[PDB]
Image (tube, rainbow over all chains, first blue to last red; front, side, top):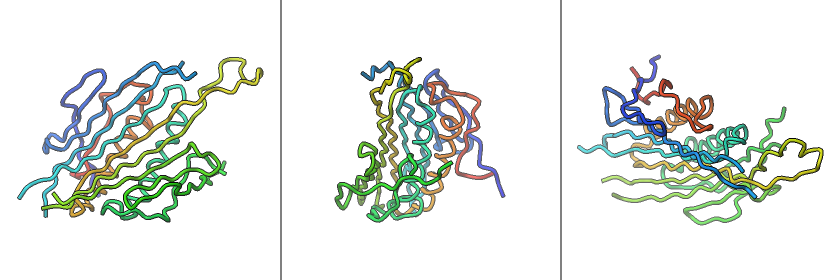
Length: 118
Length: 127
């Protein structure tokens, strides 16, 4: 079946790029990065802000469906921050992708997991 | 190696917010906070936050010397906002967002603080 439509960078700065669908210009994904020295008791924190926007017809006006993720941790521990992102997705999936959290309701019995293993 | 991710237990609860933590490492938390609102659509904003206290790397010769390093805070927050009416497409947007973040962060260099302007970013729409 079909490939996903490619998006093109429309604004491009060292620290922030905005991609949009050239045939649906309201569809956007942007990435903005902030690197900062932090003393922990000497690391370089990177805070990455990732934002997806889609304009969706109400079943007439469009609503803004938006997803904003911020990932924040030292570059030095980027290996484990990757594992944190994996587990974050998995835990979000549990509630929203295959649960009812997108309807506004939490499942108290959801199997939420750490990045650590037994 | 192990695929047995440690289970986390709800420690605080409200109708709109649960915090889960690892009972063997209580500083590891995952929280889900949801707000539903009539606005005619029923908007839902869900905020999902992951926290780990991660030892900074030991310097050269640190293991030998028995150094225990202080922890940093590794945090990931996602906020998903859209009407319950279009939840199905909102789920498709979540799959796509994960994909686009993976391109830059999971297998790119965005976690080092640098963007690849040639990265293959895609819409949830198909051709």
